[PDB]
Amino acid sequence: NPFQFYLTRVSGVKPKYNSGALHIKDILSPLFGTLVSSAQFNYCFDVDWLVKQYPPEFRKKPILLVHGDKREAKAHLHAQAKPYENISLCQAKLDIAFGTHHTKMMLLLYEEGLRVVIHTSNLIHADWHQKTQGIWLSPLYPRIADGTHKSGESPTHFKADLISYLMAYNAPSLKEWIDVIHKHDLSETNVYLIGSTPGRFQGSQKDNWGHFRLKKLLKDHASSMPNAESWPVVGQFSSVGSLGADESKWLCSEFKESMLTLGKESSSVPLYLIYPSVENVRTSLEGYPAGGSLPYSIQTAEKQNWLHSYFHKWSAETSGRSNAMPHIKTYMRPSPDFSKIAWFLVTSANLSKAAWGALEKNGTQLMIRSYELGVLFLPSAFGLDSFKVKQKFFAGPMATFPVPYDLPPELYGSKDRPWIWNIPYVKAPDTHGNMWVP
Ligand SMILES: O=C(O)CCCC(=O)Nc1ccc(C(=O)O)c(C(=O)O)c1
């Protein structure tokens, strides 16, 4: 396959549904490269667990943890790492209120080259145990010879775009990684980077980040087809922010408008949102504790009941993962019969203004609160007009894209409710015999 899109291993499914999956120990294995230094960008860390995932021969190599924690949370993380002299920390600045360092990325420097991993999992045991999570694995990027002058750039501009994303941190530990990336040849990269960084972006910079970055890439590198109005947008996520009092405030006005862009020329497009129901969580492999990683609050949800008529159940028979609750986030543009897709995005970004950006100042400024990162698969980057949807995720041309959940998405039934993580569920027990009492 050209796509190098993987799911994490799920404990409890039959082997055929893990044969093409990756555990974190597989990613860090010596078979992927001889490690000399790594950077782990994430939100939540279990440092003791994390070090144990590296091969024993690599456990003393330098590790940089890039996080967004402040105050007591920051002190707790430092305390976790202090036993390991090889671990350094970089606190990503979050100068806008209510922002998060959400990006999940590994930079893996080897004797043999460099690898970039952009994924969706926190660095804790539960996130790699029984969840549906997504991974993009870069090629092994070779080092550019000393004294050789070449760009090392891909047709998707991934090298410059990754350096630009890291430059936004203004961090000395990450300038070191920028210098590493400069010395490597990333020309084989066929995905586009879509990042979010905190700030207020106008004019020259509005297209750099968030949903305007997505819009720019779709305008420049996708084409509009006849009956494009009939091609749905699908969004799939593990959390929801405050979107406003009605759909015109952000969801269907600027977010959907960016996602329905195709091509350069100047809405009835259906919008599917996939988010686990209470029943999805109750009957999942983890049971109700899966909902600890689906942090949709009642305070937020009760202000936007209009949103839930867009919600569709989690179903993933294609990958054997209907009972592995999703912490992956994906967005895509299927054809009206869901047999093809115009593009596919895997990302850390949930359905929230903090992650994707919200327009300010009479539409002239895009304000983003958080760090996010994802990769965009466009047919033009593979010499294609569209991707065929792979019928079974782990089955056998290779030009079919492995969509990890079922299409078409199934609307909530009249008795279904979205998972809300801070109210109790005491009517029916989960797969472990328990109720949920927050
Ligand atoms: O959107 C907003 O305005 C706030 C909504 C609250 C929220 O969703 N918090 C959250 C934090 C960390 C992670 C993670 O890194 O796993 C996740 C997740 O991805 O589920 C979610």
Image (cartoon, rainbow, N blue to C red):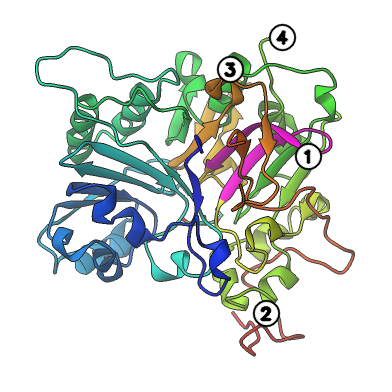
Are the residues flagged by discs 3 and 2 in contact, CB closer than 8 Å? no
The numbered dot on residue 265 is 4
The numbered dot on residue 424 is 2
Q: Residue 110 in the image: state x and y as whole percent.
A: 19, 43
On the image, numbered disc 3 is attached to which residue?
221
Question: Which residue is at the front of the view, 391 or 78?
Answer: 391
The amino acid sitting under disc 2 is Pro
Q: Which residues are magenta?
A: 329-346
Q: Is residue 349 among what the camera can see?
A: yes
Q: Secondary structure at mark 4?
A: loop
From this view, report whether residue 138 is shown above or below residue 183.
below
Mark 2 residue crowding within 10 angstroms, few (<14) / some (14–19) / many (20+): few
The amino acid sitting under disc 3 is His
4 or 1: mark nearer the eye? 1
- Picture quadrant where residue 278 is located: bottom right
The numbered dot on residue 338 is 1
430 displayed left or right of 205: right
